[PDB]
């Protein structure tokens, strides 16, 4: 069992790093950048109607 | 009188108009087109013109009719397909050779040439009458007289003359009321303005259901008549199918089908389907179509008409509610109606503040919806009527957090979900438990307990299975599981069944979407029972693989029981399901030991 | 003179300067319909009126005007309690009106006397899950942040009805001796939803204790924004003059914010993010100025607004700004609703800003703070334990997780799950707390003083 | 009738009341050239015109105008076919006027009977991937959603090529018994690609059967929107008077949409959501108006529009508004393209709702809608099984997910991958689909009636 | 004439039509104080002015206007170093006066004579990361991209002070033969900043070396925009007339851009992407065009603008625009700063596309450019490996990856780590760089030409 545990721990240590370092900042950058562009289209329209 | 100052789109400006009301019907042009002065800024009137423009010139006379835009309510509304202000389509089809009314041509809302059979009421010479009272009837519909000839709301006086039975026309006089001298002559049809709601004596509690016939609808929360209901769509998730299927199962005495700004092939489809398709109880003669009044607008018609469509429909639903008939208002889709308000907002030259949709949108979406409900019929004779609005809603901002969807969820009480991704795998309606809620649940479930179903118990448990199953599924994806507790597998497994039997239904296979409310109770009963045995078996010891395999033969049968509908008797609780229950317990014993 | 024109619900009347700001004017149509309006703006040689009555069918040459000579004020009396009104204070109880003892300004109030002694004493609602975890003090602004996958309105009937019945249970603890009144405002309500609240208060014997204002989702926007303004004034008259605690329940804040978006572009001004006004705030603040303890220091206006987000959208201006003024919020879970736990509120993202100072004494315990800590931390570990269990199994689950697994189901089924007419003060909540906790050993309960614990485990 | 000003290509004319909506004017330039223009708006004591040939040479007092006196109408001939025509007509493209048999209004004012009559029998596009999954019926509008970074042009070309090759296969099927006509309206397309379209019609030997109207992206914006309107009017003539089945290809809807935005930057009308007109929907609907089944069942016009997604999202205005009108959609696939596949569409975002009821029998089976549904279900899972592999590994994968992975590949390179001169019968498509689908038991297949699945397994 | 009105930084004058564009006018306050402005817009019988100084206190008929009748030009002298000036065309510090021998316009073309021949002479900062990886030339434009957690002022000063000691070592080498001049302009920064800078220049050398323009944050936005223009006039004269190389340090460039943003908000001018003007491109350009070698070709203006990024994003409009225009990019990293590296310059995205113009070869090695490319390439691989070290561990990374992780660590801590006064010659840097390359084997250094690797190792 002991040899079997050693083989599994390595797959498991890899995953804990993988999520934090890659996934979480990829989600952050995508969401915020699209949020910012999306609000811009809406704001300029108001200014053009007003003008 | 007035003069056309400018023609800008389908929208017309006219100068020299004063002392006019803001819903006045106006005749624009030298062709005498229908139009409606929504607003006036000084002398200039903006008019929504409900016919095309391709040759309207300035300097042409504009004549006010001296009254609002109204609709005519009375005999011969059934079995006719109308546009959004009501013109009889059939008469046009032979005569003009057109379906979209061309300029130079106009016809009035009801027929003039058709005589009707008039039967006297309960009232006689000298009797006082007021709004929503029954002055007579005309025999229309398959199964009952549906047309009660009612005195229009807010009008009163004494009837000096009630005419005798015979056949009469609807431009012909048959009643006179005296109240301030002779009040007026009345005909069969009576007038009411569409932008103005009808009054009711009072609002009443919803407790009566409508049989939608849709197994997934009947299962997860109550089906309500008097209802307020939304179903999300997106155009390509089986939504049209479940609407026409819904029109056929509806068990209401009258159905008013409303095309907001639809496909146009579908406005053909519902027309062809109605006279040759049989209703659930089955009518006598032209089942669905006799019971149906149709307002049909395609996108291609004038946006002035598409704006009006929904109003015409609710005033018809409301008249019928006051007749003491139970009515289904089926509307598809409100977002197209909202898109129509938006088309007008840019053309008039308004200021939108809701992503290019008008600021006015929120007050109009709400005002319209509040007209549905169960209520006590307008008038003295006392009857009960209802209008249940089943409304489709859809994106329009492209988001799901766009104004259209924000306003609609707030005003509605019932939401049953639909997901596009699952719908593609073919399991529509593919209800999202999380977005779904019902307020009606408590009163409706109390009613159903009296009616015989033990429903409420199952309902919580149906929801409970689907909820835990959802959560478990993210945990299988996220960690990338190497094991599961033996109970959790059962939860997931029992949810899969729910998917097939309820959620997977096809509205053109009537073996695969039809169950009465009791049949629905029995099928769900079987599932909830399976979960109950299965949870106990693991507890007493037995492996999951043992549980699944030994249960085996009854597990196949329940899966495959979605291919049934009443056809073994006129009975709503079957031997089919009752036999399964005892066999299921027998199976449980095996699993356990 | 006559009406110059109409564009939207805006009516442009050609008049000199004769009405003062906010003066009601009566537009007299000759067709049996009299309509009232308020000048929204007065400008030179023109005034802009939005009509209370209708919105369309106005003449531009046959209308005549009369000046009422009275700017908008609310007739406030206290024989208003036990009566149903509409969005302009007219009765829908039917029968003769109640009239006034005062006409008080609705515009921001003509005297504004609100707190510079922070909230003390505890207010209970009648639900253990709200009281212990999210404690509310007299005049403290804690709203219920809700979503559209829940019936937000039901949960709202429940807090109103059960509130002020707690006050007699407190009279027995001898924490209260003063008469409690309740002010209810329903904004953008459906008929069916509206009747549901009236019938519920009627069962409890709370109807006599409350006044209800209904503005329906079919009545003008202007009428709808006025609806909370009238309600905040009634509560204030009772707090000030007669030294009463009044709890005002403002549902639905989204209806009110939406109404403001309709009047944003009605006006000649330019909105902010996502089309919602940048001066949305100014308006919201008007509600909030009336909120707090009145000078006299034994009367208050306590406020619970309900705000519904579309799908918990915090991209939307409305929860982000509203959340700043207020001191905490109560977050409701769809996940619990779906399981069939009702009420389905989750106490873990929920907050009460000042909680050791949002309670009183003699109607709370001092053990209140200690239990709020214990209850919270174990429910959170339990949420973790559910997810864990699924991966690891039960044949490899930790002994601490088992206690946390059980704790998760009992906290939900005892503290959160409770009946539609159950009532709770802090003592009752507190007894139920100790029975959940009893199962953990004393050495796992360490956020609690050894004193308290040896007495209540 | 002298010029007041010119702002943009839009021209402000002073003239006194006379012109009707969409009345043509002749612009007399001082260089001795007459150019045509349309009144977009007629007003009091001015009309505003936008000119179809350029904008050059507009002066104030050196220009004069004279009226055509006639609203815009198409000079229509049925000998128009076999020839290359243009919006205004040029002699250098060999077609300086149609030489009219009838003048019909382009707005279908004489008559326009459509959309109360239901779609008839199935028609072959020769592509298996469209025909099984989506039902293309005579007298239906089903659009092609296309995207950038992908030659959308190539897909339009494959449709043109395959049109007229299907029609003898149908004549035997009894899907056809009347003539076949292609009406090609090109607007805003690249010049190089326009020439590739012209060569495709000649090669097939289908030049005779088609009429071309070509509008460039250097030809003015009002002119650009009117060209598809001309071509649909021509389709109505053939379909109704001489009972032709018309397939009209209208490319590229993106160029139409753009035109809408640029105009109305100088009218009273003022664009909607993101600078795209709120009345963009009205424009669209005028194109969809002259499409559908025809009364009395003399012929049909069937329409296949080509839309290019410019941002590569369908949440953008051009796909979004158009999609609500349309009866389903067929959306392309970016990923297949990169691989090298042609035609590179995918089936997961592609759905036709009216599929079961529309179709005929005797060259499209009863099992057609059944099998589509099954093919999508296995594909949804296959796509997801790829995604779980990326993140975690073979950790959440299993025997079921592993099958699905195999399925996604075999389907992509066998069903979707075909030739561009391959004519595929609806009978062929179904035969191939079943062969592929053998990968799971009969008991795993329950998205199909157990009756049907035994016959055809 | 007299002030009509005032709306923000815009002033409405009711005047007469004789004024020309950017003609100075002086506003006489009732205090008898005169403040200067220039007409931004002129119309018939009226003007809009933007006043440099102030923006409030401006009256009506108690105030008066007086015309100067000279459009703004800056009084430029060559005796400007050592002399204290204020950013307003004169010292308001009471520093030594400006004098004039020419008055030169700031419009962006006075007599402007620039590069028909690109930079070829190397100018060093004494800092390896700057010089080796990107290089600096006698016309080079390099943006310092800085942050709100980096100290922007310390790096700004660092680059300038160390480039003054190196630059005479380069004069002796015959890289130069002409003077060095510094023009330092601070615009609208804090007092704390301003003081700091002056202190830094004194320590290293003197303040005789540099000329100072000081502008205070309390002074308007309109002042801030003129502040760099004043710097440009100073530098162009020195290069043109007296064949001096001029080095301009322009802090803060972001300060200037926000100012532009304010005169479109309180103007009716509609802004572009992210609320930053549409004509933002032109405003920025004006600074950057007036760079390169100056006629005679011994004079020059070389630019180092200093940008502080507020969000620290590379999607913000200011860093993006600047980058396309400028001949290089120098990115300074918060993470290096934290770790203890000074200067803490990250070269991962530092790039020059005009890399050839930037390097030298007649007073620097020819090998300089060849080594730099290899270094950058090997640094980048070393970063790809760093992310992979966190994920995968050392449990699968390759023999080649291990060399690249070592290189990365040795590279930060030796090359980029330099004393506060320690200056490195460009030749010595090569030797350091060769130490960094030396650990990799001859098969890993395969991309480089064989000739160079066998020669120098």
Image (cartoon, coloured by chain):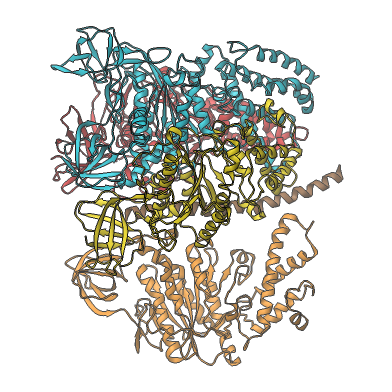
Chain colours: A brown, B cyan, C red, D yellow, E orange
**Viewer-proximal residue, E228 or B412?**
B412
Question: Relative to residue D452, is residue D45 depicted above or below?
Answer: below
User: Is any atom of residue C449 visible in this view?
Assistant: no
Quadrant housing the C terminus of chain B:
top right
Q: Seen in the image, is B403 located left or right of residue E387?
A: left
Q: Quadrant of residue B60?
A: top left
Q: Seen in the image, is B410 located left or right of residue E7?
A: right
**Viewer-proximal residue, B518 or B465?**
B518
Question: Relative to residue E262, is residue B370 depicted above or below?
Answer: above
Q: Quadrant of residue D37?
A: bottom left
For image coordinates 35% across by 68% down, the residue present is E220
Q: Give the percent coordinates (x, y) of residue C203.
A: 42, 17
Q: Quadrant of residue D47?
A: bottom left
**Viewer-proximal residue, E169 or D373?**
D373
Question: Relative to residue E81, is residue B292 depicted above or below?
Answer: above
Q: Give the percent coordinates (x, y) of residue B386.
A: 40, 19
Q: Seen in the image, is E306 located left or right of residue E44?
A: right
Q: Give the percent coordinates (x, y) of residue B544.
A: 77, 28
For image coordinates 55% across by 56% down, the residue present is D202
Quadrant housing the N terminus of chain B:
top left
User: Is any atom of residue C372 visible in this view?
Assistant: yes
Q: Seen in the image, is B556 located left or right of residue E246?
A: right
**Viewer-proximal residue, D323 or C107?**
D323
Q: Count numbered badges in the picture.
A: 0
Q: Give the percent coordinates (x, y) of residue B84.
A: 35, 32
């Amino acid at each position: 069992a002991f040899i079997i545990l050693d083989e599994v721990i390595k797959v498991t240590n890899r995953r804990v790093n993988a999520i934090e370092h890659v996934i979480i900042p990829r989600t952050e950058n995508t969401i915020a950048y699209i949020n910012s562009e999306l609000d811009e289209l809406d704001r300029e329209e108001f200014y053009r109607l007003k003008k | 009188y007035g003069a056309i100052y400018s023609v800008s789109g389908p929208v017309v400006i006219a100068e020299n108009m004063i002392g006019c009301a803001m819903y006045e019907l106006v005749k624009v042009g030298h062709d005498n087109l229908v139009g409606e002065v929504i607003r006036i800024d000084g002398d200039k009137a903006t008019i929504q013109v409900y016919e095309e423009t391709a040759g309207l010139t300035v300097g042409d006379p504009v004549l006010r009719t001296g009254k609002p835009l109204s609709v005519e309510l009375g005999p011969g509304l059934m079995e006719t397909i109308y546009d959004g202000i009501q013109r009889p389509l059939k008469a046009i089809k032979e005569e003009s050779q057109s379906i979209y009314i061309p300029r130079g041509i106009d016809t009035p809302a009801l027929d003039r040439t058709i005589k009707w059979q008039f039967t006297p009421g309960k009232f006689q010479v000298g009797d006082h009458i007021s709004g929503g009272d029954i002055y007579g009837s005309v025999f229309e519909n398959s199964l009952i007289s549906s047309h009660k000839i009612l005195l229009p709301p807010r009008s009163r006086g004494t009837i000096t003359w009630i005419a005798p039975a015979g056949e009469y026309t609807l431009d012909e006089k048959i009643l006179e009321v005296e109240f301030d001298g002779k009040k007026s002559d009345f005909t069969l049809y009576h007038t009411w303005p569409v932008r103005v709601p009808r009054p009711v004596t009072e609002k009443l509690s919803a407790d009566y259901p409508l049989l939608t016939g849709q197994r997934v609808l009947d299962a997860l929360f109550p089906c309500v008549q008097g209802g307020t209901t939304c179903i999300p769509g997106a155009f390509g998730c089986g939504k049209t199918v479940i609407s026409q299927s819904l029109s056929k199962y509806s068990n209401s005495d009258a159905i008013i089908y409303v095309g907001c700004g639809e496909r146009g092939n579908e406005m053909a489809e519902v027309l062809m389907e109605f006279p040759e398709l049989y209703t659930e109880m089955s009518g006598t003669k032209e089942p669905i179509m006799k019971r149906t009044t149709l307002v049909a607008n395609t996108s291609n018609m004038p946006v002035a008409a598409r704006e009006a469509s929904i109003y015409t429909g609710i005033t018809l639903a409301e008249y019928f509610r006051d007749q003491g008939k139970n009515v289904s208002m089926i509307a598809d889709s409100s977002s197209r109606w909202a898109e129509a308000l938006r088309e007008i907002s840019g053309r008039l030259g308004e200021m939108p503040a809701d992503q290019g949709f008008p600021a006015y949108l929120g007050a109009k979406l709400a005002s319209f919806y509040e007209r549905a409900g169960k209520a006590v019929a307008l008038g003295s004779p006392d009857r009960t009527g209802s209008v249940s609005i089943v409304a489709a809603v859809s994106p329009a901002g492209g988001d799901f957090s766009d104004p259209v969807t924000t306003a609609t969820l707030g005003i509605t009480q019932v939401f049953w979900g639909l997901d596009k991704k699952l719908a593609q795998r073919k399991h529509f309606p593919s209800i999202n438990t999380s977005v779904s809620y019902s307020k009606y649940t408590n009163v409706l479930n109390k009613f159903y307990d009296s009616n015989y179903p033990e429903f409420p118990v199952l309902r919580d448990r149906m929801k409970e299975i689907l909820s835990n199953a959802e959560e478990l599924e993210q945990v299988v994806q996220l960690v990338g599981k190497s094991a599961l507790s033996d109970s959790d597998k059962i939860t997931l497994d029992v949810a899969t069944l729910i998917k097939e039997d309820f959620l997977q239904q096809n509205g053109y296979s009537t073996y695969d979407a039809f169950c009465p409310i009791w049949k629905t109770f029995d099928m769900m009963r079987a599932f909830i029972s399976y979960h109950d045995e299965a949870q106990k078996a693991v507890a007493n010891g037995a492996n999951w693989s043992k549980l699944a395999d030994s249960t085996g033969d009854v597990k196949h049968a329940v899966s495959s029981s979605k291919f049934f509908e009443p056809s073994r008797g006129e009975k709503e609780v079957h031997g089919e399901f009752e036999k399964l229950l005892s066999t299921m317990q027998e199976r449980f014993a095996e699993s356990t030991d | 003179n006559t009406v110059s024109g109409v564009n939207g619900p805006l009516v442009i009347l050609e008049k000199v300067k004769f009405p003062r700001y906010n003066e009601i004017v009566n537009l007299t149509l000759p067709d049996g319909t009299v309509r009232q309006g308020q000048v929204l703006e007065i400008r030179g040689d023109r005034a802009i009126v939005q009509v209370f009555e209708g919105t369309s069918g106005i003449d531009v040459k046959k209308t005549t005007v009369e000046f009422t000579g009275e700017s908008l004020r609310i007739p406030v009396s206290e024989d208003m309690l036990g009566r149903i009104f509409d969005g302009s204070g007219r009765p829908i109880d039917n029968g003769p009106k109640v009239f006034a003892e005062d006409y008080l300004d609705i515009n921001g109030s003509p005297i504004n006397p609100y707190a510079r002694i922070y909230p003390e004493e505890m207010i209970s609602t009648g639900v253990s899950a709200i009281d212990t975890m999210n404690s509310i003090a007299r005049g403290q602004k804690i709203p219920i942040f809700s979503a559209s996958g829940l019936p937000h309105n039901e949960i709202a009937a429940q807090i109103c009805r059960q509130a002020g019945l707690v006050r007699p249970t407190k009279d027995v603890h001898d924490g209260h001796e003063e008469n409690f009144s309740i002010v209810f405002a329903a904004m953008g309500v459906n008929l069916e939803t509206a009747r549901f609240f009236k019938q519920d208060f009627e069962e409890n014997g709370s109807l006599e204790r409350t006044s209800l204002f209904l503005n329906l989702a079919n009545d003008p926007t202007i009428e709808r924004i006025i609806t909370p303004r009238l309600a905040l004034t009634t509560a204030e008259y009772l707090a000030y003059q007669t030294e009463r605690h009044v709890l005002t329940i403002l549902t639905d804040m989204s209806s009110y914010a939406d109404a403001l978006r309709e009047v944003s572009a009605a006006r000649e001004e330019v909105p902010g993010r996502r089309g919602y006004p940048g001066y949305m705030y100014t308006d919201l603040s008007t509600i909030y100025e009336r909120a707090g303890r009145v000078e006299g220091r034994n009367g208050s206006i306590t406020q619970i607004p309900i705000l519904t987000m579309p799908n918990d959208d915090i991209t939307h201006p409305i929860p982000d700004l509203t959340g700043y003024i207020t001191e905490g919020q109560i977050f409701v879970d769809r996940q619990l609703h779906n399981k069939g736990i009702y009420p389905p509120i989750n106490v873990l993202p929920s907050l009460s800003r000042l909680m050791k100072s949002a309670i009183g004494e003699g109607m709370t315990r001092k053990d209140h703070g200690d239990v709020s800590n214990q209850l919270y931390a174990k429910y959170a570990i339990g949420k973790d334990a559910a997810a864990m269990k699924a991966v690891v199994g039960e044949e490899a689950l930790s002994i601490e997780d088992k206690l946390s697994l059980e704790f998760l189901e009992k906290f939900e089924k005892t503290f959160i799950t409770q009946g539609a007419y159950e009532d709770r003060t802090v003592f009752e909540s507190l007894d139920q707390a100790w029975s959940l906790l009893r199962i953990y050993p004393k050495e796992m309960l360490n956020r609690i003083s050894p004193k308290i614990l040896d007495e209540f485990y």
